[PDB]
Image (spheres, rainbow, N blue to C red):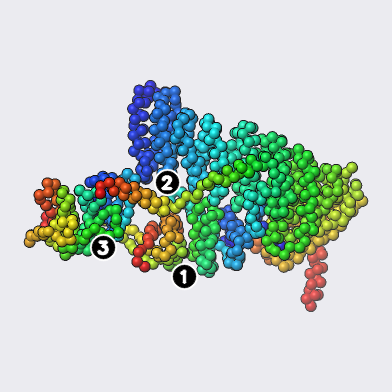
Amino acid sequence: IVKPNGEKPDEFESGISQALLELEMNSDLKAQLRELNITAAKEIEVGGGRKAIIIFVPVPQLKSFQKIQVRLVRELEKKFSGKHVVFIAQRRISRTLTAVHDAILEDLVFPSEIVGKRIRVKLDGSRLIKVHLDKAQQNNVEHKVETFSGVYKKLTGKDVNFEFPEFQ
Amino acid sequence: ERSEASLKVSEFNVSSEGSGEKLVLADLLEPVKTSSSLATVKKQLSRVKSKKTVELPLNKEEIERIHREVAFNKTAQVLSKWD
Amino acid sequence: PLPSIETKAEQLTKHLFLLLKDYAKLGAARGQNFHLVVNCFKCVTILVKKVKSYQITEKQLQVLLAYAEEDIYDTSRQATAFGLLKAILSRKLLVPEIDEVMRKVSKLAVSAQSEPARVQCRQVFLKYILDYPLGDKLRPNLEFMLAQLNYEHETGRESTLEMIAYLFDTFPQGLLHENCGMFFIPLCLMTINDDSATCKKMASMTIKSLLGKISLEKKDWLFDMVTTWFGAKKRLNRQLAALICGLFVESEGVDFEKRLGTVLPVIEKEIDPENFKDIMEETEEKAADRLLFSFLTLITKLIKECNIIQFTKPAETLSKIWSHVHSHLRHPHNWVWLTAAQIFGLLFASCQPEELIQKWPEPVAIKFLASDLDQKMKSISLASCHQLHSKFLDQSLGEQVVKNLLFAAKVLYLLELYTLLWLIQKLSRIAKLEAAYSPRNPLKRTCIFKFLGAVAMDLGIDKVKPYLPMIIAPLFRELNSTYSEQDPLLKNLSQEIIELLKKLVGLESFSLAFASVQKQANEKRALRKKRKA
Amino acid sequence: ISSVKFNPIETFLLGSCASDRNIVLYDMRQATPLKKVILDMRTNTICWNPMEAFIFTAANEDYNLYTFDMRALDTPVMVHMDHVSAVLDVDYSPTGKEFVSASFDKSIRIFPVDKSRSREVYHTKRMQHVICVKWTSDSKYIMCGSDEM
């Protein structure tokens, strides 16, 4: 299930592939998992003790992974000890740096959509970036905003905060 | 032409409950012949079942929220004195 | 040893209590305030531990208990009061508030996400059970632990088994007998109904620790439960019985013969091929395979823990058992024939090859091979040749198959002196056919090449010479190839094996043998140009 | 956050105003906020009633003043509607029956707490953009600070 760029799979990636096979044949998700594979998997630390798994999947399959994103996240977080799991497409080996960052940010928060962006300049001269998410999916991704900020900081290097506006 | 989806072979890697039926605790106790020791074992296991297992800790957001309702109710009870 | 410590010890105590009063409340340890609280609890612990000098009075210990309780309930911060909490337990403070605090620590031992947090919570709870005289309340604290075995997350479930294994090591014999039935049966479910592998292994070890220190009369009572599970209708119940009975053979060791009489009739029914001939559902196929795999692992445990090979008295059942294992060497499931190959591998190591031909009461297993020895060794070699074609083939899988082939190769040789060429020709054809179709896959060429080197090394220098051109013939083909320069794994393997051939056998005779392969290459191509025309 | 004020009665309570047009109530002992209410426009300053523990008045950008009961934040107790520009500051008389408000329009008004209209308005030609206002402590005088220095 892991197809890296001509390299040996890591122990964590191998474990992710093992869990994916277990879901593939034992559970009732065979019709979708059979055609799907991942590229890489990584674990990072956020929020002073929290842990996040990033599953890098190939781009042409990403849309298909969106069909069963919620089920896979729910199963994998239970398989692990509550660590937050996110699925992200594999962009870096077309698109500029900003486009790649925007695509990563879109994939990172997938159940909720990005509807707006604000920058506030404080009196000290610093800047704060706020990204607006839809109100319809607030309860599903409300607890993962710190995880999203940490993952985006780790991958891109930029500080981003997440909010839910009242008006659509 | 079949495999168990685990690279290493072990009795702990069998991955039971994948297909078929589930096995509850009562299926172990039912067939064995009745005895006084079996009766007290059943009583002990029932008393164990009576105890409550620890729930998963809630997310930080709803923990903070519940803190807000608790504190607000306490403050409202305090403020009702001045009416 | 500072003489000013005693004079200033009174002033130190007031300062430390003020900081604990201010900084141990809710939300007062964020940022820079966190490290102050960490070192504040450490310095207080030193004062409590050293009772000999400037000892803290028992009333003050109750105050420090309240501060420690407030710390562990603070969800925002990490708990830092576990070191102090152990020190109070060592001072034997007897107040009703001790019991309520220990309930929270017991809950934290399961539900804490931080790994060091669970470790420290376990040591406080274990210190509490052993060292306090509350006998009546000791019973509820044990049944609470068993209820915690159903925790949804793996880490909390692992921590419970850590605490249980410690109590089995430290309780007296009398307490262990009273609560034997409480622990054993729920732990049996964990070995089968758990989702994680490492919890299943830990559940197995704590059962064995229970079986080690338990009295013999209680062992018989526990085993009747297992024997009842053996006859149970449920397919999971039977494989559970095999798995639990597999734990006894280590705990019994060489004392399992008293129970061994009833176990053998049960096994021969399950491993018999007639049961699994016709199954129309994929669910039942996996149910059947996991049942069969569990029972074969039971046989492997019997072979190593007991001398089942060197037994003669249950001759009728052993003959049926040893033939069913042979029938499962062709099973499609890779986990099945791998264990079956392991069982037959255990025979071959135990019996020297010249003994079998010399015979061509007695142990049934030896008699099983000795009768129809030529037919048996042909089937073992043919089954091993089939296992190479299996798609689920690995280096670990190949090594067991190769070792079985080595024993079959030796036995056929000494039989000829009183089909080795047929065996070598069969494996040589496999190497030829694979490189033509798929040079990308190196797995089968690796096992065949390792087989050739070991066969030559076992044979004497004069004896390899009649077989030398056939051994080196597949090696020459992979020495130079188009894919060989791409992936040199096969080419390096050939160069390594050739060097041992040069050391083992005379270099001139090796050159004579190598040239003999070279010339036969020359005529074969020369015919090929005629075939081209 | 623009302003924070301690409650003179039940001294552990706090009030606050921020830039997304909300008002937040805190609690010092339990170290947590209590409740949040969002209005149409930003509030500039908040003031507690010195005789009624659960009453506070907010100076808002929508030319208006809102008096609230902190137990029931769903609706304001009263609205005060005499100003024509943004209200910047409010202060209560020590008797707790009136308050005085400053606005970006160059005037200051006195409102009764139970009425919706101002009792009086003060102005001067040299006075412009009153920024801060304090009722004096013997309930006899009013002082204002403006940007003509």
Query: With respect to residue C74, does A147 lie above or below?
Result: below
The type of residue carrying mark 1 is Ser
- In the rendered image, the residue lying farthest to the left is D125
Examine the rendering and report whether any part of residue A22 can be seen: yes
Q: CA distance from mark 2 to mark 3?
A: 36 Å
Kind of residue at disc 2: Thr
Q: Mark 2 belongs to which subunit?
A: C
Residue where numbered disc 1 is placed: A94
User: Label 2, label 1: how many angstroms apart (C-alpha)?
Assistant: 47 Å
Would you name the residue on which mark 2 appears? C75
What residue do we see at 27% from left, 63% from top?
A: D40
Pointer 3 residue: D41
- Taking C414 as reference, is C178 left or right? left
Quarter holding the C terminus of chain C is: bottom right
Residues under numbered marks 2 and 3 in contact, where contact means CB atoms less than 8 Å apart:
no
On the image, the x and y values in percent for residue A130 come to 36, 61
Which residue is nearer to you in this view: A59 or C252? C252
**Residue at mark 2 shares a chain with residue at mark 1:** no
> How far apart, in angstroms, are the residues tagged by discs 3 and 1?
45 Å
Left or right: D35 with respect to D9? right
